[PDB]
Image: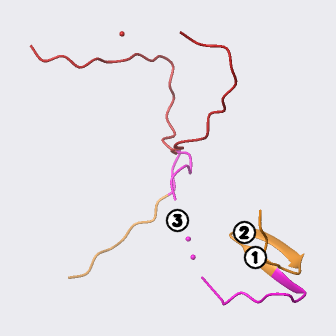
Amino acid sequence: RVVVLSFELLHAPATVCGPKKSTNLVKNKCVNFNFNGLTGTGVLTESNK
Amino acid sequence: DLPQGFSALEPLVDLPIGINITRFQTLLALHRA
């Protein structure tokens, strides 16, 4: 049982899609982070907001 | 009765249907406003 999967792009908008990965977050350290595509550099702290 | 006051509409759902909508209507529930 083998299936030939097709990944096709046509004259249709790419409205519909998917993604994932995960490392234990550090704290109180100057590090560069990538949160769900939001990338930056700084120090992460617990907050009450 | 739209009263006087202020209220915000928190987003409920967004969907990537990706079709063209030009008209609209509504439907009702009756078993034989």
Which mark's residue is nearer the viewer, 2 or 3?
A: 2
Discs 1 and 3 lie in a common subunit: yes
Residue type, numbered disc 3 = Gly
Q: Amino acid at mark 2?
A: Gly
Residue A9 placed where, x, y %? 51, 56
On the image, the x and y values in percent for residue B15 come to: 51, 44
Q: Which residue is mark 2?
A: A37
The answer to whether the residues at label 1 and label 3 have Cβ atoms under 8 Å apart is no
* Residue A40 in the image, given as x and y percentages of width and height: 85, 73
- The residue under the point 87% across, 89% down is A29
Chain B colour in the picture: red
Cβ atoms under marks 1 and 2 closer than 8 Å: yes
| The magenta stretch spans residue A11 | yes
Q: Are marks 1 and 2 on the same chain?
A: yes
Going 82% across and 78% down the picture, which residue do you hit? A45
| Chain letter of the residue beneath label 1 in the structure image | A
For the residues marked 1 and 3, what is the alpha-carbon distance in whole angstroms? 17 Å
Tell me whether marks 2 and 3 sit on the same chain. yes
Q: Residue at x 78, y 77 (%)?
A: A46
* Label annotation for residue A34: 1
Task: Read off the magenta span.
Answer: A9-32
Residue A18: mark in rendering: 3
Q: Chain of mark 2?
A: A
Chain letter of the orange region: A
